Length: 340
Ligand SMILES: [Cl-]
Ligand SMILES: [Cl-]
Ligand SMILES: [Cl-]
Ligand SMILES: [Cl-]
Ligand SMILES: [Mn+2]
Figure (cartoon, helix red, strand yellow):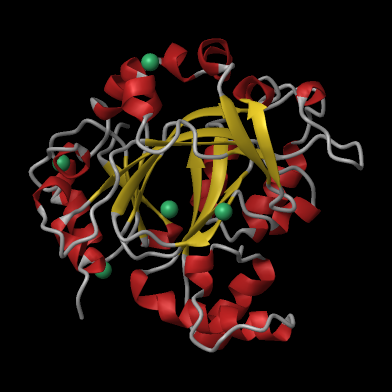
């Protein structure tokens, strides 16, 4: 039976089922005021699927110059064509190879660049912005988005949206690597999974994905969306409450010191964007500092809401196209204030 919502993370995470339901705000706002993330499923059913394919991005924009990141070692591949990324998105025999002769796991950096999404891709911009869930919060001029209404005493977000494109992590060694390392944002964000590419060539890569979700601490209900509904899983997130950010800095300064880093006692390991919390570090955070997070699997068409100030990291299971919009809710405006 169709239902308005359900719970993940053993009741700690709201999952809304109908992205365009005019009554969603009634269920959302209680959870949001407490500093919790929220998941909304089904956004892919609202979109024009032909606008969000890797082959279309390659055909239309393939001659642009871009930099890539090697996710395994953080090395930068400078000044290549954007088709060199897109044509290896699903077909492994077309990926750029490292020295060892293996195909690389690549992230496309800052594309489209800065604030240029709307000018470069007007039809994509319209399709996304007209179908975002919780539109009073998430649209540029929504009644509950303060972004356009605040003075310079507040850090204001850039004009969006921002696209996040990267291959899936593959091997057992890759389990400990991030697609996007642990960081925080002073604005709220909504992050939509618009495409998941499950490859061919080294296709049959199903079993390392299940060990990653299990060791990642995913709940039993999330393990059912795979085995029962056959939905496409994109990315594993870990999100932490804004109130736990300083305890996470204390753990990472202790671990940086153990690993022979020489950092001043006040340096900020979250702002540095240099860490990925693997199974070992997530257990140490819980046991030694008393901090629990939310482990979230983002499937095709899932919208993740990330509260301002909340530390979070992202690990792609398969090749992903994500599109994210920043906003400033009244519930979390304290996090972008420039005084006290
Ligand atoms: Cl808060
Ligand atoms: Cl377009
Ligand atoms: Cl709303
Ligand atoms: Cl990163
Ligand atoms: Mn972020």
